[PDB]
Image (tube, rainbow, N blue to C red):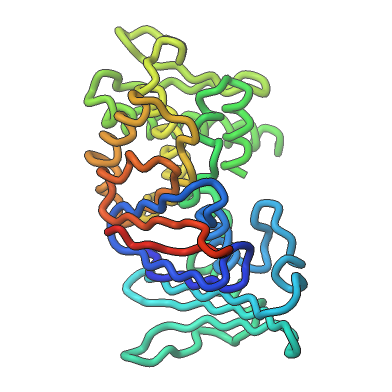
Length: 313
């Protein structure tokens, strides 16, 4: 799964926004209110309409009147280039137009009936909603929530991962354990071998998380800020791996809304050494200092009342 281009017109501060994504780490920088957040929303909606994206109302697309709303998304998956186009007609004309095409030579050919129903059905076979929304897309607050406490950790796990009672209990225990193994490997990678085990223990509306240092279970209080963001990211990505079985695309939506020299220096190290192994990463941040660790930099800002895109690299 690799995004190529998103076009968004007449959605929030986007009058006519085109963003082109490439290989490697794509940093989308912008101030609060720039439109960088709504851009991601428009991607998710373009992919999975009419399924729920966050708290966004259908009416915001079908109703908020005058001027057509338009979302066009080109992406590649398994050697095929696809294009999803959604048009919400307004200002005289009315209704909805949906199409999904694949590129055949130079021609875009419909891959299913141009209806939202058929396109939804196809997208569930290509890349299911729950996988994209929980494995590929990492929502703001999740990484911090993992590091907050045992209860909040429990909440993030419950969110991301969603005779019979026995089955359910077993499934949950197994899930937590597998995530622990995966996170051990990743976090081990991230701290150059300092730690090589991450312990995860479910315990009554709680996910206990412990670091392994000197073969003793240490609480996350033992960690500096850096190795903190490392552990939270490693745990979050372990959950993505658990769900999807691989990470080919990763969308990090404001992973560090607050960041210090240390946290930032660590995220930078992690981008440079580790996240560059992922075919594409899209990182949305307010932090200019991340630019150095990125392959491609796109600044989004509000100018003359609409989002404007500046390609920095």
